[PDB]
Image (spheres, coloured by chain):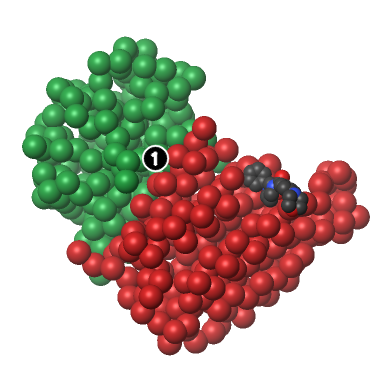
Chain colours: A green, B red
C-alpha cells in the first residue's frame, strides 16, 4: 500500500486529442479511401473534460489533429517544466489500428512513438510522477521500458463512456485506477476488449476530497 | 465489487516450463552460437512451485522444453476439462527476443501463439475464469481480445519478488494487481509490463 502523489492544485494537464474529420485522410491515402468521419466523439471528449476537471486536472484539448499536428503538441508538454505538477494524462480519440493511431491526414503515429515522448531521460521534471495514456481506437511494444506508466488502450469497431462513469463514481470513494479498469473491463464484456498494460510502481488515485 | 471465484481444490493447474540446457540451440541455430545456459533458473522454478503449491495449485513442472514440446504441453491443457478448476496458471522461464521465446533448441514461439491457445473457443472448459501467464525471458499482440487474461511478462529480480510478495500478501486477501504493482517498485531501482483483461478482482485465498 503505497500511493502516488495525487494531491496538488491543479494535479496536472489532461491532454485530450479529439480527431473527427478524416477528410484529407479519405483523399491523400488510398487504402483509407472510405474512412467514416468519427462523429459522436464530442460525447467522449466532453465526458473526458467533465470527469478530469472534477479530479483537478486542467484540460488542454485539441480537435482534428494531423500526425504532425499530434506530434508537435506533445513536445510542448515534453519540454514543459512539470515540476509543479503531480501527474500527466493524455487521451487520444481517433481511428485506430494494430499498434498505431491515424491522424486526420490519414497518416500514422505508433502508440510507442507517442508514449515514449515522456520518459525520465526525455521529460525529467515528470519523473517518478505517473504518466497515463487513455486511447480509444476504431476501424514492438506500446510503452517505454520504464516505471510509472499506464496505458488504457481499447479498440472500437462504450469504453470511454464507462471509464468516465467509473471515474466520476469511484474516485471520491478512494478506489485506484487499476480497480476502475477491471470494473471497466467487466462493464463492456457481454468482445472488443480494452487491454490495460502498465508499469506503475505504486497505487494511483485521483482524490475528489 | 466482484472477485473471481477461486474457492477450488485443486484451484487449477500451474504450468512451469523451465528452459535451462540451451545446448541444442547452440547445436543447430547459428545466431544462437553462444547462447548461455540459464544457470540459476532452478531457483525461480522452486519458488514458483512453493508459491503456488501453497496457493492450492497442482504444479506441473517441465524442464528443458523445445518449441514443439511447448506447443504440445499447452496443447494438452488446452483440450483439458477444467470444469472443476477455477484458474489456469502457466509459468515460462526461458529467453528470447522482444516477442518470441526460445525453446532449448533455439526455435522461436510468439507469446501470442501461446496465450492464444486458451481462448474461450479453444478451451471452452476455461471460459470466464482467469488464465494467468508469467513470463521471464532474458534478452504484434500479446493476449487475445477475450476477457479474463493476465500477462506478467518481463523483458530481461522479477520472479523472486513476484513470489516473495505473493506468499506475503495473498493471505491478507490482496488483489493480483496490488501484488504486481508491488513487485514493480522492488524491480524499479528491465521493467515488467502486465497487460490484463480481467473483469473481476483476483485473489488466491490461503486458507
Ligand atoms: C535471465 C536469467 O537467467 N536470470 C535473471 C537475470 C536478470 C533478471 C532476472 C532474472 C537469472 C534467474 C535466476 C537467478 N539469476 C542468477 O544470476 C544466479 C545464478 C546462480 C546463483 N547461485 C548458484 C546456485 O544457486 C544459488 C546461487 C545465483 C544467482 C538470474
- Quadrant of the drawing holding the C terminus of chain A: top left
Q: Position of residue B76 (x, y in %)?
A: 62, 80
Q: In the picture, residue B104 is in which quadrant?
A: bottom right
Residue A101 lies, in percent from the top left, at 38, 37
Find residue A62 and report its image quarter. top left
> B67 or A56, which lies in front?
A56
Instruction: Please tell me how crowded label 1 is: few (under 14), some (14-19), or many (20+) other residues with Cα within 10 Å.
Output: many
Q: Residue drawn 52% across and 61% down?
A: B133
Q: Is residue B2 above or below residue B174?
A: below
* Whether residue A162 is visible: yes
Q: Which residue is mark 1?
A: A200
The residue sitting at 18% across, 25% down in the picture is A8
Which structural element holds mark 1?
loop
Q: Chain of mark 1?
A: A
State whether residue A24 appears in this view. no
Residue visible at 58% across and 63% down in the picture = B48
* Relative to A110, A207 lies left or right: left
Q: Residue furthest right?
A: B27
In depth, the one of A4 and A159 nearer the eye is A4
**B48 versus A87 height, above or below:** below
Q: Is residue A175 above or below residue A117?
A: below
Judged left or right of residue B99, residue B184 is left
- Residue at 19% x, 29% y is A7
Q: Nearer the viewer, residue B100 or A71?
A: B100
Amino acid at each position: 500500500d503505497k500511493v502516488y502523489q495525487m494531491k496538488s492544485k491543479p494535479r496536472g494537464y489532461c491532454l485530450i486529442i479529439n480527431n473527427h474529420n478524416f477528410a484529407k485522410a479519405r483523399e491523400k491515402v488510398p487504402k483509407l479511401h472510405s474512412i467514416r468521419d468519427r462523429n459522436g466523439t464530442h460525447l467522449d471528449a466532453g465526458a473526458l473534460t467533465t470527469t478530469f476537471e472534477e479530479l483537478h486536472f486542467e484540460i488542454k484539448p485539441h480537435d482534428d489533429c494531423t500526425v504532425e499536428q499530434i506530434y508537435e503538441i506533445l513536445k510542448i508538454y515534453q519540454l514543459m517544466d512539470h515540476s509543479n505538477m503531480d501527474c500527466f494524462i493524455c487521451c487520444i480519440l481517433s481511428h485506430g489500428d494494430k499498434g498505431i493511431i491515424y491522424g486526420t491526414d490519414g497518416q500514422e503515429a505508433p502508440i510507442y512513438e507517442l508514449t515514449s515522448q515522456f520518459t525520465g531521460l526525455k521529460c525529467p521534471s515528470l519523473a517518478g510522477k505517473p504518466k497515463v495514456f487513455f486511447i480509444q481506437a476504431c476501424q514492438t511494444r506500446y510503452i517505454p521500458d520504464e516505471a510509472d506508466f499506464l496505458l488504457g488502450m481499447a479498440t472500437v469497431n462504450w469504453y470511454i463512456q464507462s471509464l468516465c462513469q467509473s471515474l466520476r463514481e469511484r474516485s471520491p470513494r478512494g478506489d485506484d485506477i487499476l480497480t476502475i479498469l477491471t470494473e471497466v473491463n467487466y462493464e463492456v464484456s457481454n468482445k472488443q476488449m480494452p487491454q490495460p498494460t502498465f508499469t506503475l510502481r505504486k497505487k494511483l488515485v485521483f482524490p475528489s476530497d
